[PDB]
Image 1 (tube, helix red, strand yellow):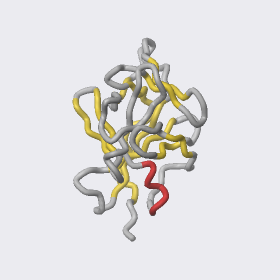
Image 2 (cartoon, helix red, strand yellow):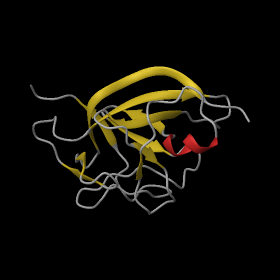
Image 3 (cartoon, helix red, strand yellow):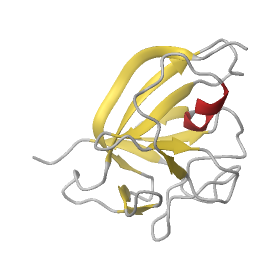
Image 4 (cartoon, one colour):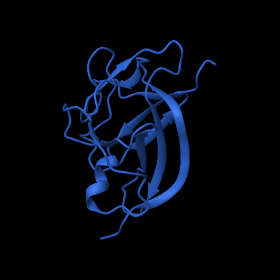
Length: 151
């Protein structure tokens, strides 16, 4: 089928925080828990790069990775936590399996949402106390924010 091939280099090594403002830190190499920054740079830092096919719908996919290791975000199913799939380097030609790493980036001010471009019913949530889960909407705070560090 048509492959979704890398569009443009977005932002990287930023501190990712939700509307709850919990900078999402990796607690384990498979599970991630969000916690409010005060140094700003305290969470594991992501790097986003958008990738492109004209087979979306009306929404575009970006790549979520932590700058440090190449653990990329897999999209599970609704209220079931986002899984850390280690797929090396941001793909330039994306065919079937890399589809776990699609994110619909809706930016509003500082906060922004990530709807799974494959399935909305997957949505990239941020929790104030619990692990970073998923839902087919939010009642989880699926806000994120690109937060630069204090000094």
